[PDB]
Image (tube, grey):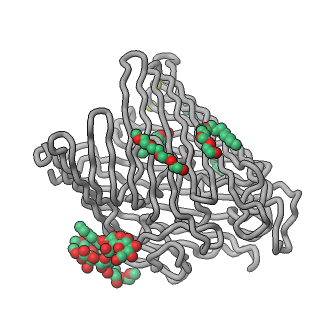
Amino acid sequence: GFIDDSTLTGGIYYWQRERDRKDVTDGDKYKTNLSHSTWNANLDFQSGYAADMFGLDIAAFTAIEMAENGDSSHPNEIAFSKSNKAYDEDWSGDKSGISLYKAAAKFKYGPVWARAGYIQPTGQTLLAPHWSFMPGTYQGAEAGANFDYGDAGALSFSYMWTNEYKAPWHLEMDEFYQNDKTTKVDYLHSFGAKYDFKNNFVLEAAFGQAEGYIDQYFAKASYKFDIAGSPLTTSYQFYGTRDKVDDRSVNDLYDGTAWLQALTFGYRAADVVDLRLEGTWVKADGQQGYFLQRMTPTYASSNGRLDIWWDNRSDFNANGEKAVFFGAMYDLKNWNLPGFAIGASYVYAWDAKPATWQSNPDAYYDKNRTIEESAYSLDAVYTIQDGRAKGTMFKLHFTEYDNHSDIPSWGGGYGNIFQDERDVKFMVIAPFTIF
Ligand SMILES: CCCCCCCCOCCOCCOCCOCCO
Ligand SMILES: [Mg+2]
Ligand SMILES: [Mg+2]
Ligand SMILES: [Mg+2]
């Protein structure tokens, strides 16, 4: 029951990074952009259900700075921002702290479930937290249902409503606003569904809104089949967004519907190497000039579901842009190094356009330009196989990112693109169980 089925788990985390970026307004100096060493640690209590109907979850984490270079930018998203509320953010520093990231009543009744309080989305909608080591947190509620039809498939759906949020690098919640940071968005809500036909074919879709401002869409089809005894997995994904401000004010983001479509393939070869081939295509006409999967435009103010992630620094999400990604991860078990893996990946993207109009354009703004970007990354991972520290993981990731233009960072009507970088991340993740 509620006591007997309780669990208490957590982890200790270590992160060290060095990233530099080209300033094409001072020669082309690769200047320090991030340089810090930071710890996290968390405790997560999840109760059982009294009478199979009522429970409680409570979880908290701390972040402790260890080193930071004076030229490191802020916030680094592993420590806490010195600005506790997202809409106060002024980019001037980072700090240590303790955050309550889960605190919720949970309910079950037949096929129905619900959660309320300080929560993460967990069902079928398109709301989502940001993830660092730990997730961001919404103030609100979600309810959903699950119906199993045996071999004929299974249906799930849910609805969530929220009026405040905090990213994992913010110690306090803030409300929602339009692009101007002052016109109120009273709530975000979303409804979605999933149908699993139990033949490896699965459909998902969802709709969301930011009150008075943005309508958001999500749809995904996936399928897998065996090729030579091993599954090839495929998916088609659609993300869309439309706004309700088209007067050419600061709050006017998109002309028409903006969207991102994607195709993915995955396959494990010779039972030893995981291969990925993926591509994306974006349309984002209007003042902003890039696609967002979240329903509020300001950095850190909320997040939305996005199943595409290439860990190659850029978002590759500019108006018109096409991108293709290839990744390989090689399991070294047959060299008798079980738990050891090495990888490499590459991206090439073309046809990236800027915003279609600008109110105070800069020297470099050219409505009809197109640009390109590319990147490649290397990866090394080791997970402890047995003993006291079984499952503790060490990871090293290197990216080299190349902007194929001379436009300075964030300039030219390309408001989400920055300049060439080199990035190195080292992390350690050490989970534990108390009971
Ligand atoms: C201009 C709309 C484009 C939508 C693209 C297709 C996305 C497929 O999934 C969307 C599922 O959403 C269902 C719509 O929900 C109701 C919308 O109407 C509500 C008020 O306008
Ligand atoms: Mg295989
Ligand atoms: Mg081999
Ligand atoms: Mg370059």
Vertical placement of 361 versus 147: above or below? Answer: below
**Ligand 1 quadrant?**
top right
| Residue beneath the point at 53% across and 66% down | 176
Residue 147 lies, in percent from the top left, at: 37, 28
Residue 203 lies, in percent from the top left, at: 53, 30
Q: Quadrant of residue 211?
A: bottom right
Front-most of 338 and 24? Answer: 24
Residue 119 located left or right of residue 210: left
Q: Taking the image as drawn, is residue 341 in sight?
A: no
Q: Taking the image as drawn, is residue 2 in sight?
A: yes
The N terminus is located in which quarter?
top left
Residue 148 lies, in percent from the top left, at: 36, 24
Front-most of 139 and 291? Answer: 139
Residue 360 located left or right of residue 293: right
Q: Quadrant of residue 84?
A: bottom left
Residue 371 located left or right of residue 410: right
Vertical placement of 129 versus 338: above or below? Answer: below
Vertical placement of 415 versus 398: above or below? Answer: below
Figure disc tally: 0
| Residue beneath the point at 80% across and 67% down | 412
| Residue beneath the point at 84% across and 70% down | 364
Vertical placement of 334 versus 215: above or below? Answer: above
| Residue beneath the point at 47% across and 38% down | 330
Residue 429 lies, in percent from the top left, at: 33, 56
Front-most of 328 and 4? Answer: 4
**Residue at the extreme left of the image, as rendered:** 4
